[PDB]
Amino acid sequence: SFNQVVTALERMMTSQQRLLSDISHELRTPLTRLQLGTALLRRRSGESKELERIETEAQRLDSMINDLLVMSRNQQKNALVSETIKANQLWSEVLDNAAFEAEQMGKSLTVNFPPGPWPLYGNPNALESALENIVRNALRYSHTKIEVGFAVDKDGITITVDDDGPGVSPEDREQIFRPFYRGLGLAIVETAIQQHRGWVKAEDSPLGGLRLVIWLPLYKR
Amino acid sequence: AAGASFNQVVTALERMMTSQQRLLSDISHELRTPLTRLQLGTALLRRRSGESKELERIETEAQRLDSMINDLLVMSRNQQKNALVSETIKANQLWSEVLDNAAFEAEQMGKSLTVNFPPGPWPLYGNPNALESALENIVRNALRYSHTKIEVGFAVDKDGITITVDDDGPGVSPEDREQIFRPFYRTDTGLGLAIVETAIQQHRGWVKAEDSPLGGLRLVIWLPLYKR
Ligand SMILES: Nc1ncnc2c1ncn2[C@@H]1O[C@H](COP(=O)(O)OP(=O)(O)O)[C@@H](O)[C@H]1O
Image 1: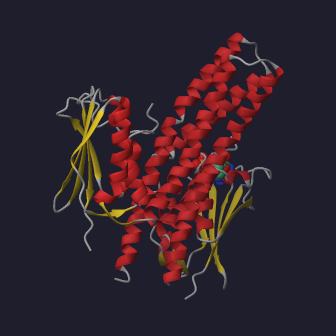
Image 2: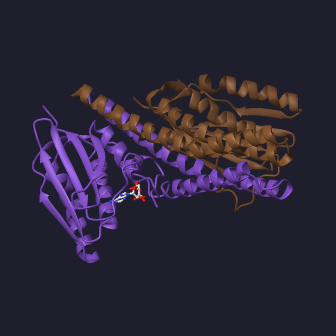
Image 3: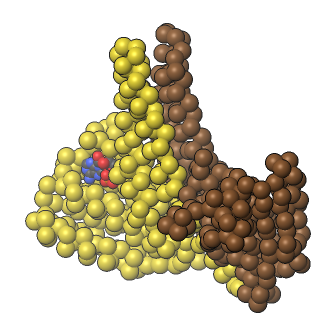
């Protein structure tokens, strides 16, 4: 029955993925026809700003569908692949690359309260890229400075990212999380952190901009 | 700790599923952004250059996609809530309520549902919510398209249960029989048989559409029995 349960859980998941790859094939059915259509028009007639725009909007859609497949598969990679990991070990490189990128922009990143050997359970690549996006995003709004701080209590780690940028109005605070924001978006992070039983909140930064608060629970055996 | 390690994995996959629920509804919301840009692009090209077989085709493929995005946005809301648990279950317990609500809905429409061959205490292993909503959609369908009557029949052998749903409605042409199972497919949301086909194939069973002796469409669900 251990095998029976394993085989059952595999089929729950493979069927979810089948349904998704079948929706994407059905969305691509007219999309490929559209792309074949522009291709024939491009050869028959000339190239134009309009035809260029139609062709790039077609790619933009196919890319989104392609992200939907991958990001779905990755959420499975994330639930099945997980381990006990220390706060300082996990995000040290993240903060080091980020410190260098600020130095290049002429800006200054400061880790006032550094992470310690604090137990976390979960996908390391997921949590690595979670803070990485918040930190890349804080390098955008910020005029000159960014500040990262780590806190720990009996319940969990609290990561706080602050910028001296323009920030966000009280109304827009709750509505700062949706994808394809033009890192990628900020809803990837919300999903990623809620996947690890944590939460994310946006606030007024004492620096003048926006304060991003990531909370994750500590790992207890 | 033998089952404590299972709960933890189940809870993880539960959170994994609800995160894939969100991701889908968010992609679908974002898909109308480039589509409108594409439609304003063809519109300007129609104005600049002339009208052509190509431009006509691109414009109709854009509509076809828009429709799908709408269907995807509706079947983003009302997601398949609280699934993922497989268990041993008896056929009669499983679909009793399904057939009872369905018998009442027919009575309201002035139509008549008949369970000629009822389900028995037959062993099944799998997600109950998945199998309940599988037949539920097939009967939802058969209630809508039928003119006056619907017939449900259960059969069992050493290999498995065979559920047959028949309606006196218009039915489907020989060509569209397999096509009605595809996502967004409609003969004229189209995600009904898409979901049923997945739910059955998941339980290593099968679904087929045929000519009904009642005059409409015959839907055949075959599931295997659970052996201890
Ligand atoms: N009982 C039926 N009789 C005739 N046509 C049917 C029947 N059931 C389904 N169809 C056709 O197959 C299509 C696909 O079915 P389905 O996936 O369940 O979509 P929907 O959610 O609109 O019912 C329907 O839109 C309809 O054209």
